[PDB]
Length: 265
Ligand SMILES: *C(=O)[C@@H](NC(=O)[C@H](N)c1ccc(O)cc1)[C@@H]1N[C@@H](C(=O)O)C(C)(C)S1
Image (cartoon, rainbow, N blue to C red; front, side):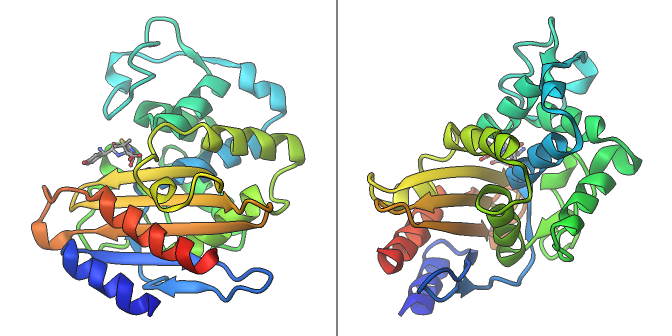
């Protein structure tokens, strides 16, 4: 029994786990704590890139953005290396998705513009996709730090799955922009030990991870069966019982995904 297996994993990792897989074709939706709020952490960077792509002509990707020492305020594997030269919008999108670069995401928020350094426009983009649940209130590093239960900077496995479905599988973006977002998530470097780890090699996986304080570990993915049948998989977790410094536990996500993959096979 699936709910029993997820609850077993919660006890194993002293965690709260949320899972959603939308209904499609002949599979019922898979849901576990799917309507409970979890911190976005870096998972927001996927719809952020979509927002930026949607808002501008495709060749806005070629615009050079400059930034300085005081803009590096969070884990930023790429932006720290290019600080002397700047990064184009396309480079920033690439880094935000593939390396979960915090500075890149902060600069992309500013590019979107408006109140809250872009967080309000980001939230408005989600509302345009019918997501009345999610909210972004802060940028990096603050967005990963809200106390357990606080609704700031949260989504739900249900809400973010439906957003990702529209972005990758549906028609939220035109095909060319859709393909850019899909390819960056396909080439993600941070996700090998999460949803990817729970699906057989002959299934295609694209994803965006998130990791935060209070043992937060998330992953949102689109997977394709060996016959090209796609599914959206959202797994979110925290370990609030260990306090602020609780270790995120990727293995929880790998195990949850293995259970999901068993049902979808
Ligand atoms: C978004 O989730 C980002 N999270 C980190 O910036 C955050 N400071 C943090 C990282 C790791 C911890 O143990 C605690 C807080 C980036 N996205 C993450 C991811 O998995 O995608 C990282 C790649 C770790 S950093």
